[PDB]
Image (spheres, coloured by chain):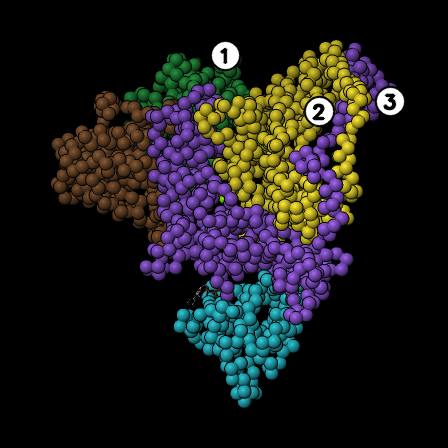
Chain colours: A green, B brown, C yellow, D cyan, E purple
Amino acid sequence: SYDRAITVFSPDGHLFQVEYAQEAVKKGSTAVGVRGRDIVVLGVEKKSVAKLQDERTVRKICALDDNVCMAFAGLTADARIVINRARVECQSHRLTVEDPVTVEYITRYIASLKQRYTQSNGRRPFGISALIVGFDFDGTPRLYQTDPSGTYHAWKANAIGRGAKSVREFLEKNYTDEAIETDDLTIKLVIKALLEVVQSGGKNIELAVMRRDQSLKILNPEEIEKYVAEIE
Amino acid sequence: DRGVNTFSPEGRLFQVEYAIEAIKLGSTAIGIQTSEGVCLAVEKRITSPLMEPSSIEKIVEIDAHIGCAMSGLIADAKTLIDKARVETQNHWFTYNETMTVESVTQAVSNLALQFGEEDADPGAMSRPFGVALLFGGVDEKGPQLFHMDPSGTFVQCDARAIGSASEGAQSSLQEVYHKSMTLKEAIKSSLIILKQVMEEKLNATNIELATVQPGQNFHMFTKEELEEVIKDI
Amino acid sequence: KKTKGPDAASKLPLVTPHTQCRLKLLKLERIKDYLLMEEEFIRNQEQMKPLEEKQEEERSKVDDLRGTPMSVGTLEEIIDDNHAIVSTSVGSEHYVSILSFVDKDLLEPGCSVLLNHKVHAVIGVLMDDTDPLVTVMKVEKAPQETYADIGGLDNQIQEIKESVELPLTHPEYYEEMGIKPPKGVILYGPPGTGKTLLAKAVANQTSATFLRVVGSELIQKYLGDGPKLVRELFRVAEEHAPSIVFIDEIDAIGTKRYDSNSGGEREIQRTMLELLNQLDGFDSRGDVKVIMATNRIETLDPALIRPGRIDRKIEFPLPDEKTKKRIFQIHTSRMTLADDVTLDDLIMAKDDLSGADIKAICTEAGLMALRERRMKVTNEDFKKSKENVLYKKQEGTPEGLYL
Amino acid sequence: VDERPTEQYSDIGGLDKQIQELVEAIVLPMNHKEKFENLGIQPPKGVLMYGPPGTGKTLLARACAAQTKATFLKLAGPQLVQMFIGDGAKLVRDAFALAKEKAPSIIFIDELDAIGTKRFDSEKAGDREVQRTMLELLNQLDGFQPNTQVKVIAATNRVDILDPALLRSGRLDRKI
Amino acid sequence: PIRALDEGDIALLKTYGQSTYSRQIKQVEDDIQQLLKKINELTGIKESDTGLAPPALWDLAADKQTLQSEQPLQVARCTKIINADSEDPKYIINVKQFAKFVVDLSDQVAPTDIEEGMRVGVDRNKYQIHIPLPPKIDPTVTMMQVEEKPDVTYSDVGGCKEQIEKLREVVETPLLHPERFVNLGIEPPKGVLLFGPPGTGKTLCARAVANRTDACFIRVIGSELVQKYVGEGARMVRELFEMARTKKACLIFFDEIDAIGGARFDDGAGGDNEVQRTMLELINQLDGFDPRGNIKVLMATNRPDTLDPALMRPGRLDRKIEFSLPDLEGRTHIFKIHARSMSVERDIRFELLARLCPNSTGAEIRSVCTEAGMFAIRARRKIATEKDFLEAVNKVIKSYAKFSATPRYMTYN
Ligand SMILES: Nc1ncnc2c1ncn2[C@@H]1O[C@H](COP(=O)(O)OP(=O)(O)OP(=O)(O)O)[C@@H](O)[C@H]1O
Ligand SMILES: Nc1ncnc2c1ncn2[C@@H]1O[C@H](COP(=O)(O)OP(=O)(O)OP(=O)(O)O)[C@@H](O)[C@H]1O
Ligand SMILES: Nc1ncnc2c1ncn2[C@@H]1O[C@H](COP(=O)(O)OP(=O)(O)OP(=O)(O)O)[C@@H](O)[C@H]1O
Ligand SMILES: [Mg+2]
Ligand SMILES: [Mg+2]
Ligand SMILES: [Mg+2]
């Protein structure tokens, strides 16, 4: 059983392996999530459709539970693994607490999973940052971000991966209650933000929407094209 | 190369020294012990306006009479908090009493520095926790304030400030604190020092304040209360 | 005296319109007119004013007393009013007599002293001994560019202007607060992103005595000549009035010091040490400001980049979106573009496209045009240039690892 | 050495078991020369003080001085090298000279690591005069029979670089 | 399919395009280019043959008197004397680089006035001896004295009190008050080498000493210590120390001694050979069978690890002084010192900037105090503000010119 200390402090007070994993999260794709008044929207900018790849198996938005979904940015394989562990935990909590999980709870579990992978022996930090959205039992929309460092936070909106900060600055100046007044405005808000990073637009961003009662819905390419035209 | 458990020419562990250094990066936190009670304050250090300031919890409760303030690898603080709560409830379950602040800190400290690489455990901790806990609570002995450093060292203190502003926050605490200080006087003095060290103008949204008193349980001030104090301070 | 010897240039006040036009014709005609007027007047007044009673018989006497082939020698410990010691190029200590023509002042030890060939005698002082390998670094034909030629670098141009132009343009602005004007900016960035362009721009509106260096010509093959060429360079800089010395490609003499084992890699270290000592050491430094350009700021020894010697580290990055269109506008002007070759499209796509790439695409585009026997660039003539100029570049991560 | 310093073998520490080895290469063979021939054994006319930096070589050197009464002869590694070709040659020739003159004395060549370096050479050989100086010193040392009494001892802070010839047989042979 | 370009093709191409007045434009430009050359050629670089004192102040003597100076007063040649045969008028001299000789003493000079070792004025033709020459004082060696007082006092050297006291204990008190070192008989430590990260005031303190040295403060321009011809450097250092041992309480500063000193080796071109020889001469002079006297040495470096051991050991340099990064109080004092001449608003809290500038050095503290009012000048104000200073700190240090950790990076709370 390999039991070497992979991540260990360094002078001036830092954890290299945690930083390095963070950059790996950066080089990924750009993913944006915003919390509306009664809707939570996630989007992603696709590096390349490739004209042969079957778009079905390359989904970078998934549902941990009927009321929780997430988007990520980083090593794919690390992302698929983390999602499986979250999915099983969601069912386990349903089994014991007899109630649907809360976005805050599942975020703590996923965050606690990553925290256990930085400090552990003979392991590598997870190379993904995850954006978790969902509607709690009370109905209040929720948005959570988790970094590889294991720190998790609640946001009105934010962006990970390549083209994160610039997008967030765009979000910071352009986010407002008026922009979150209508569902369409929220959806268009997302698209413009990605367009701030992605070039082609309409055909290079995949969008998904979660409502209070309805489960996750992925916008059709026609719907994405229609919204892009409306913005223009 | 340079195993975690290594000794320097001075007899100093390398990892423990680094971890203590990392503490400085964390935000400020002020804890003052008074006969009327123990008060804690902290700087939230909001990264961005989008982030919800409610989800940055720098002051948690361990029991109805114990509170903690953190600074450092907040990700590392989580496991330390969980152990403290379990130990408190285990003590209540067995002895049908409330664990004293020193006992809880001693239990938490015993978790700090229990790390190794070879022949330790299938998944033991490899590295030291980089976080400095200010334990505050009321026990049979009255109000108690204990600071814990990453080295597993806990020592009751009358007034202390941890974080990036510790040096100078301590200095200010020196010029003002005195034995007969009341809780309100401690809270105000704590708020001023936090205001001085905080670059951003101090308002009601960027600072967490909590207090524990012999009568009341652990209490975390709400926005309405926080505004009232900073109004005069 | 500290003569503020300018670039001795600007003889082209600059024709305002660049499009072949009679306005250009008339203006350049005015330029020629004044130039011819000057030539005529100088020749005429040289011929006229019959001062032919010249030569100031007395100066003829002095020249007579100081014979033919005068020799250059180094003055040494001066003994008496009418006596001093000299050292010829062979390093032989003659004992000469200072004649009356020599001003007893201005003759200090170490000052090159003229001599009479036959009877070694200090005949006159020489205040121009600048190393013929150093005087070749004074720009005397100002490069033809203006801050408007460069584009898309506002923030990165204002920074240099606030330490190479304003401090001598409105120096009251600085003293009013007492902050000493920043001295020395290092322009570090990826290849082909400006750097030298901004250097030439600041050379143009100099108002000073620009000195150009290479970054390798300083290194010399004779032990010590290295760490004396730099000394001579900066001595000349301080002797002349306000100056800016551009030590381009400082990556050459800048490698991080190390406990070496060779000799050349120790002489180079000594050269860097001389540079550091003089730029910020026991001394001072008058109105001498140093501009350094490099491709790799991570290699420079921490020391030659310190916030007391090289402040205001500019960060010339790869051009951004709007800057790309600006540079295309500035580099496509003097071409007869067609009506469907608007450049608002060639931008984007590749995230790697520098200013050098832009100029290459613009030039191998006109060259492409001169292949269908046309002088009006075409959109195909531009779309066939991206596949011929931007190539051989490296690539990145394998798709799938990330999105 | 006109000043004739004032060191004595009680102002020096730990210098025993090597102080005596220097004694029987400096004082005894010069003071009482007869009893060395009494058997027929002569202490080689050279002792090299190889030892890590700042261990006390010059200390024992000035100790052998002062209490010598023999007009200690002093030199300097860097001083030997000179500008005009052969000036160092004259310096060394004379240095071993005026030693037969004022016959009673002992010469100490400090910083020997410089005047003599391992036999690297330049294809130009223009900067190889130091090698000529070192060969001259070696020749002088060779031309010396125990009948004459002018000892030579020198220190080298780094015995590594010394030319593995100055230690051959009859040149500096005893090591301390 | 790229067919070449024919001569007719080029000809037509040169003439189908808008050039109403363009041939004339090019011709006139060429005329201007050829006219500049004529203008400068006829106004070429003249009036540069200086070196002539104005034969007006001494105009009267600036005449046949000069010729009288010439002709008589034969120009002599310098030369030393290696012997003076007693009771035998013959002398032996070594001129300098030419050769040695045997010389007779001219009648005009009494033999007593001429001694062994003094410089004689031998004449050409037959090398006879004339008016002796005083001992030389080399120009390079004599061009090193401070001969001034740099405008830096101890007060301005903030942020380090222990360091300044340590330096003062060896550079000032042991010369300005020998009493304290006799009652205990403590030998004043001599030789202080200052370490420190690049830029901390290591040279600032050296300059500060020069303002109260009340003696010579020869500043070794290390670059001058190395010259082409062998032995030049050793002679340079020997003359340095010989002039040192000629006054009372001389202090010699070797700024950036890393240039002249380094680990010895014989691998690469036999090391530096000449440079190492100069280093060895310096070491011998500092310590050896020739007590130095009343001369002290201060040396500074960025990396002491690359110093030759025979020079780092005590004796040559005793009082090593770390110059570590300033503490909080040190930073506050440094800001206060490099802010007292700035038009800054009174309500500025300098105790906060100090915390916000961790692991910085004095040069950084300056570059922050400056470039702080620079933003004010950019805004066209006249009294900078605390916001300006804070923005300067964020744009100078901590984040300096590169801040990679930013995108969703808030793990330290
Ligand atoms: N933003 C820009 N605007 C205008 N011209 C530009 C721009 N960027 C590059 N160029 C042009 O690129 C050409 C290549 O030379 P340039 O001075 O730019 O190189 P550089 O950045 O100094 O290169 P090096 O890395 O080799 O020192 C110049 O003629 C310059 O005009
Ligand atoms: N063994 C020792 N006991 C006492 N003092 C010593 C000893 N060794 C050296 N010293 C002291 O060291 C001081 C400095 O010179 P030192 O004797 O160390 O030179 P060294 O070791 O001979 O030098 P180097 O070998 O580099 O020429 C002397 O004044 C001497 O008193
Ligand atoms: N502690 C300090 N207090 C006040 N000023 C300081 C302090 N440290 C540095 N400075 C300032 O830093 C400026 C730059 O220092 P300088 O580079 O000349 O010397 P140094 O720090 O010794 O570095 P170097 O290694 O280049 O010799 C000085 O003008 C000085 O005023
Ligand atoms: Mg140049
Ligand atoms: Mg050994
Ligand atoms: Mg210095």
How far is the residue under mark 3 from the one under mark 1?
Answer: 57 Å
**Badge 2: chain ID:** C
Specify the amino acid type for callout 1: Glu
In this rendering, would E145 be left or right of E189? right
Whether labels 2 and 1 belong to a single chain: the reply is no
The relative height of residue E143 versus residue C308 in the rendered view (above or below) is below
Q: Is mark 2 within 8 Å of ligand 1?
A: no
**Badge 1: chain ID:** A
Whether labels 3 and 1 belong to a single chain: the reply is no
Q: Where is residue E41 in the image (x, y as percent from the top left)?
A: 77, 27
Numbered circle sitting on residue A230: 1
How far is the residue under mark 3 from the one under mark 2?
Answer: 22 Å
Q: Which residue is drawn at 29% across and 29% down?
A: B195
Q: Which residue is drawn at 61% across and 73% down?
A: D98
* Residue that carries the numbered disc 3 in the rendered image: E7
Q: Position of residue B160 (x, y in %)?
A: 25, 38
Q: Position of residue C87 (x, y in %)?
A: 68, 50
Q: Does the residue labelled 1 lie within 8 Å of ligand 1?
A: no
In this rendering, would C33 be left or right of E184? right
Numbered circle sitting on residue C363: 2
